[PDB]
Amino acid sequence: PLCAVCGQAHSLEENHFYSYPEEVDDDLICHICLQALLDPLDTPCGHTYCTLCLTNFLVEKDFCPMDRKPLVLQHCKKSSILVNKLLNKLLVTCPFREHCTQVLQRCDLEHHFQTSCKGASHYG
Amino acid sequence: PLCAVCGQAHSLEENHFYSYPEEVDDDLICHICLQALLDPLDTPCGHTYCTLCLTNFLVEKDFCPMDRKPLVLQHCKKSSILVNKLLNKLLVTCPFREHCTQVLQRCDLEHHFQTSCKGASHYG
Ligand SMILES: [Zn+2]
Ligand SMILES: [Zn+2]
Ligand SMILES: [Zn+2]
Ligand SMILES: [Zn+2]
Ligand SMILES: [Zn+2]
Ligand SMILES: [Zn+2]
Ligand SMILES: [Zn+2]
Ligand SMILES: [Zn+2]
Image 1 (cartoon, rainbow over the protein chains, first blue to last red):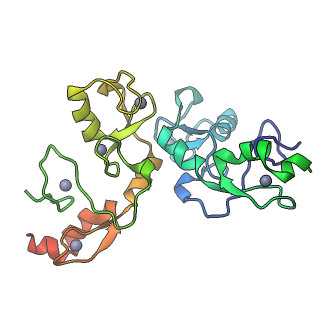
Image 2 (cartoon, rainbow over the protein chains, first blue to last red):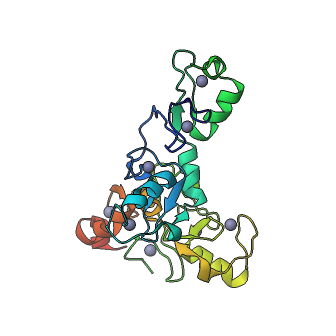
C-alpha cells in the first residue's frame, strides 16, 4: 500500500521512509531504526527516538536503548521546536524516480505530491 | 578579567563568548543574545535559549520571547543530549590570535588552553 505522505510502500504501523541524497548528521539518526528521526520523542534521561520506534520498543522491552535505564512511555515528551526544524529541512529525493527527479525539504514532500509531482499523479 | 574557559574578557555574570569561522545554523542561535546557544534550556512551549540569557531575561520580563506566552524559570528544563552534541561540535577560532591559529570544536577549547596553546601559556 503506497503512502500518500511519503510515497513509499509501508503499513500504517510503520514509519514514513525517506531517501536522503546528502548525508544526515549521525546525531539526528534514531538509535532504534538507524534512519533520520521522525516525530522525535525525548526520554527523561535526555535521549531521543522516533515516536513510533520508542512506542514499539517499549511494548516488548522496558529500558532506554542507549543507557539501559528503566523507561516508560508516559514520561517521554515531544522534542523541542529546534530539533523539529533541523529534521524538517533535511533534503530528500522524490521516490517516484521513473517520473520525477525532485529533491526537496522533507517537510515539503507531501505538498509536492499533492501539487506538482508527475509520479504521484500517475501513482505506480 | 580573562576567562580561563573561553579566553575572552567577560564577567562571571556573562556568557562565554566564541568566534565561529564557519557559519552557525540559524536554528542553533539563541533569540535573546543572537549567539550560538550555550548551556541550552527548553521552555514548556518548546523554545530554547542559553541558560544565562533566559535567567537574566526572566528577572525583568515574564514571557517567552518567541511567542509572548507567560513563562517562569522553574518549569524550564535542560535541552536534550542531541542538542548539546550539535552545539559541542561547532568549530571555534582560538581567541589568542597573535600567538595561535588553532580551530577546534567548542567543547575542546578549554582543554586546548590547558595543554597546547601558546596564547594561554603567555596570557595577554
Ligand atoms: Zn509514509
Ligand atoms: Zn526510529
Ligand atoms: Zn537514555
Ligand atoms: Zn516527485
Ligand atoms: Zn568564558
Ligand atoms: Zn543566549
Ligand atoms: Zn515559547
Ligand atoms: Zn590557542
